[PDB]
Length: 188
Image 1 (spheres, rainbow, N blue to C red):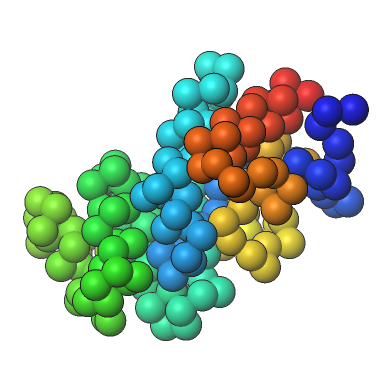
Image 2: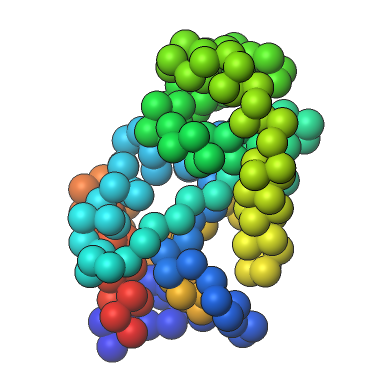
């Protein structure tokens, strides 16, 4: 075959019912994730090739960066609740990995303030039970699927993208291969 289990993707032994259609996991501490977001624009290029009627979900994970990793998962929950994912993703990545100016929850908060979210509004989101269940969702989805590494993508709770088995000589060729795989898996 051209697409083979164990080559461009692996199959979950233990499939996850009711899972989001396209599910991505990342961490702001994760170096390949930085690349995926800033250099490759993976999420975006996958979306451009997905059939439509397809919804795309992205969650943060706790297992990198100890205490700040958790803060970052709660902040990503705030971002999702406020619909400001596209305004904070880049400065969070660069704050954590490039400039290293994010060292505390208050520094994470600064990024949202600088992106124009209001103090009252951030602190209210931060502390809301709607954000608590969104944190719960992020953790449950990761727990359901065996998650020990990022970046990670799952399709319909049964297939996991396997970028290790795609050519990396060319960054553009890698992305298309990656996205076409998602679409193949999607139509499976």
